[PDB]
Length: 125
Ligand SMILES: Cc1noc(N)c1-c1ccccc1
Image (cartoon, rainbow, N blue to C red; front, side):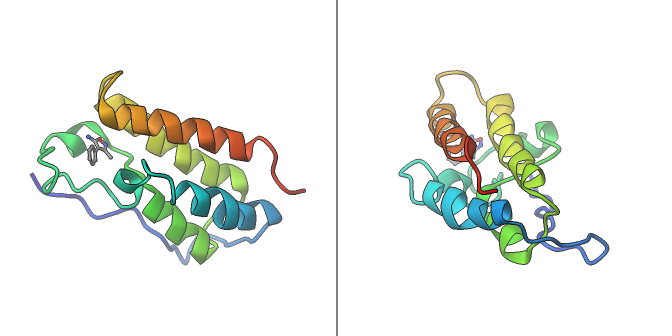
């Protein structure tokens, strides 16, 4: 089954913004999570062809991944931290929707989500 086009990482109709919190989400939150041993499945859009998940995009209609989020942050695509946080949460939720409790990929998402929540608990002012 085909992959859809990946989510946009720029949008000229959308206003950009740089905030201390968005800087921090890239420099600290994203870039540290990225180095985690369980980060690799989330560093690019789900390749449903390669992974032999032909029903992935029949189920997941708002795909998200850290590769896309990283590019969005580097673009200053977001208006605020909450928009970016929402993308992280979409990424985790997608994983829990498509997969089942106890699955290896779910254990990976669960661990990353905990680390993510740990790091966004306190943001710059
Ligand atoms: C990401 C993701 N979301 O659902 C999966 N099965 C995966 C995945 C699982 C194993 C390797 C790579 C990706």
